[PDB]
């Protein structure tokens, strides 16, 4: 829409109040013109036709409970855009300031969210397994990192490349959650998963086995379900990334942590310069070693930590 940029206020899914960038032209729309070619949030109105209607609002105050998922999707896409711009000097997901589009209220009782190749889509959850999925900043950043991958390495979504694809999204979703300093942790989806239970989450990067996911290459899933285990075998890579960052001893192998910032620089470089559509775990290890080598020298501690971490999860 063509209009005047302004700022509205509303409440997100967890009840927190925030300012959001809107556009005024008869109605106030969820269109943020301050970032690249714009961030646009749509109402799918409980249907599965996409994108639905650009979200329109009469007075620029988004406190209705129907508005909550739209507020957070809108807001957390802006935070993710800022993270990639400020930290990695990347303008939007294609590197050219492509418009970011999200639809909320997709379908009825839908317990998921996803990047479909052209935009983000968020279900509201059934209210028991999940509440509206855009309330989780690590979920929004996970899904938006899928767009980044698609334009760079292009990892195919099955078997080991798909598991790498998923782990990359859990890693940057987590790094965006630490960047926004929203109660950060190494768990995925804990703000929106099972509103009745405290403490749990969909997956854990610091201890994947807590939920039954593999934390070592000898425990990888080899069947056919979940596209060859793309959400399951990503635990091996997540555990490796957690160790590079934080350090620790795993199956008897000791890793000195080098921190989150270097973790993000190494994986972002590996992703945009060395991974290809069919890379598998052993090529990820080589990409990450080469990236850390490029940035810190082949005899740095950084290179040494990336090798110990992949040795600790059994990836050679
Ligand atoms: Ca309103
Ligand atoms: Ca958290
Ligand atoms: Ca989290
Ligand atoms: Ca829970
Ligand atoms: Zn994913």
Image (cartoon, rainbow, N blue to C red):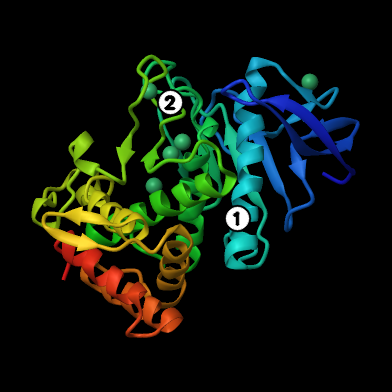
Give the quarter of the image for residue 130: top left
Whether residue 208 appears in this view of the structure is yes
Q: Quadrant of the N terminus?
A: top right
Instruction: Please name the residue that numbered disc 1 is placed on.
Output: 83
- Of mark 1 and mark 2, the one earlier in the sequence is 1
Q: In this view, does 269 lie to the left or right of 285?
A: right
Q: Where is residue 290 in the image (x, y as percent from the top left)?
A: 35, 80
| Crowd tier of the residue under label 1, counting other residues whose Cα lies within 10 Å: few below 14, some 14–19, many 20 or above | many
Q: Which mark is residue 199?
A: none
Q: How many marks?
A: 2
- Residues at marks 1 and 2, CA–CA distance in whole angstroms: 28 Å
- The answer to whether residue 5 is above or below residue 284 is above
Instruction: Please name the residue that numbered disc 2 is placed on.
Output: 110
Asked which secondary structure carries label 2, the reply is: loop
Q: In this view, does 21 lie to the left or right of 167?
A: right
In-front residue for pair 257/137: 257
Q: Which residue is drawn at 47% across and 47% down?
A: 143
Give the quarter of the image for residue 25: top right
């Amino acid at each position: 829409i063509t209009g005047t940029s302004t700022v509205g206020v509303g409440r997100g899914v967890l009840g927190d109040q925030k300012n959001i960038n809107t556009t005024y032209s008869t109605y106030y729309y969820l269109q943020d013109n301050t970032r690249g070619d714009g961030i646009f949030t749509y109402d799918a109105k409980y249907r599965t036709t996409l994108p639905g209607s650009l979200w329109a609002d009469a007075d620029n105050q988004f406190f209705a409970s129907y508005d909550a998922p739209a507020v957070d999707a809108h807001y957390y896409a802006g935070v993710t855009y800022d993270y990639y711009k400020n930290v990695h000097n990347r303008l939007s997901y294609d590197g050219n300031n492509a418009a970011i589009r999200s639809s909320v209220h997709y379908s009825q009782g839908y317990n998921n969210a996803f990047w479909n190749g052209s935009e983000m889509v968020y279900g509201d959850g059934d209210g028991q397994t999940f509440i509206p999925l855009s309330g989780g900043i690590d979920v929004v950043a996970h899904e938006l990192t899928h767009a980044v991958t698609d334009y760079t390495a292009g990892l195919i979504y099955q078997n080991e490349s798909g598991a790498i694809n998923e782990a990359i999204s859990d890693i940057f979703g987590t790094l965006v959650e630490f960047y926004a300093n929203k109660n950060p942790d190494w768990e995925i989806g804990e703000d929106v998963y099972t509103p009745g239970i405290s403490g749990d989450s969909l997956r854990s990067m610091s201890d994947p086995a807590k939920y039954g996911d593999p934390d070592h290459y000898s425990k990888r899933y080899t069947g056919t379900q979940d596209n060859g285990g793309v959400h399951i075998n990503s635990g091996i890579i997540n555990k490796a990334a957690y160790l590079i960052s934080q350090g620790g001893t795993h199956y008897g192998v000791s890793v000195v942590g080098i921190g989150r910032d270097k973790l993000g620089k190494i994986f972002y470089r590996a992703l945009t310069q060395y991974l290809t559509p069919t890379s598998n775990f052993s090529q990820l290890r080589a990409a990450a070693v080469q990236s850390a080598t490029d940035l810190y020298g082949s005899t740095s501690q950084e290179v040494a930590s990336v090798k110990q971490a992949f040795d600790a999860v059994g990836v050679k």
